[PDB]
Image: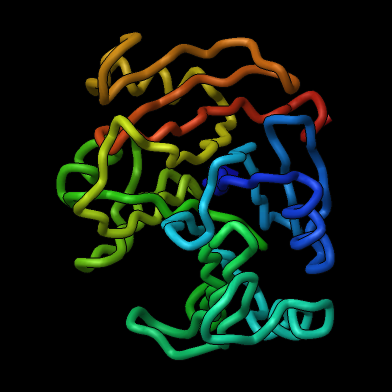
Length: 125
Length: 125
């Protein structure tokens, strides 16, 4: 497929891998500079950034899911905390200004991963 | 598909759209906050960032292409300059420390879009 995949900053490649692995993300490439973490085609292609702050972080990607609630079942079973302040954290499957619904993962590097539901009434029927 | 797509910063949504449009990127969503530019599944989902510098820019995504040289045919015909210093610019289909070959687009917002060739000897055969 002509497919756009996100290339995000990570300080340690063992610490950021052990965050996403338990959610079903397979480690398909790793050197010292590049690290590909993949749940099907959830392809997070991390670059080695040692001087990054989590608090001043604009960095983000939309994980577009075929069930949005299955990723939220998996996060509360494997260990990611449901909280207003702090990092790492999860916010809930909420109703949005576009069409349907979106949850929000914030990782150890501050990274706002927007969990979108895909539109099965238009995209299948 | 379980598919990871990049969410990048843009200052004007007419100026950054008229950059990618001529390379085959269809404008499928635009409000004031979000802008989706898409060549097949090259889904660049831009957020409105007015205080961004192009020179201090870590922001980046891998465009994984089925011909890498077809995107480089299209850039030199429609108008993107081949140069060492400056922005916007293109660098060439060069040999890399991972497997095959990668070119590099740098846009008006400093954004390092890494143009990867997909691996048809392993992924088809």
